[PDB]
Length: 101
Image (cartoon, rainbow, N blue to C red):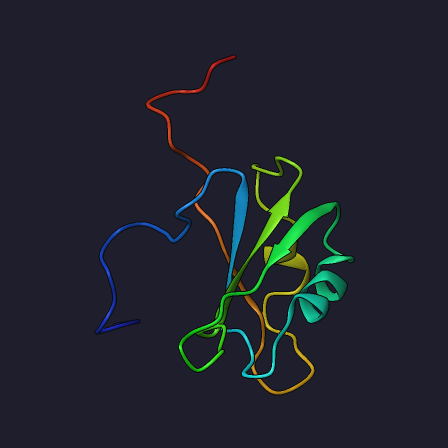
């Protein structure tokens, strides 16, 4: 018994060119992200969401250089921060019945 209240599909993504980041801090910003992912390799752009209260809902996105055989940040960071809440990187890598080549 690991989790009781969670969706029974293999992983989180909603994207094929964009990296999902969750567990984000309450005072987080694109600047805190661009600097954490500076270590994780080529970053193309960042994304911060903002609720009716102006909050990133504890999640974000980052655009990255087709890094599909595991995103390096899932290994580099995954459990680190500066305000209180450790960054959690999430991904899937598949929207195809089979590879091309």
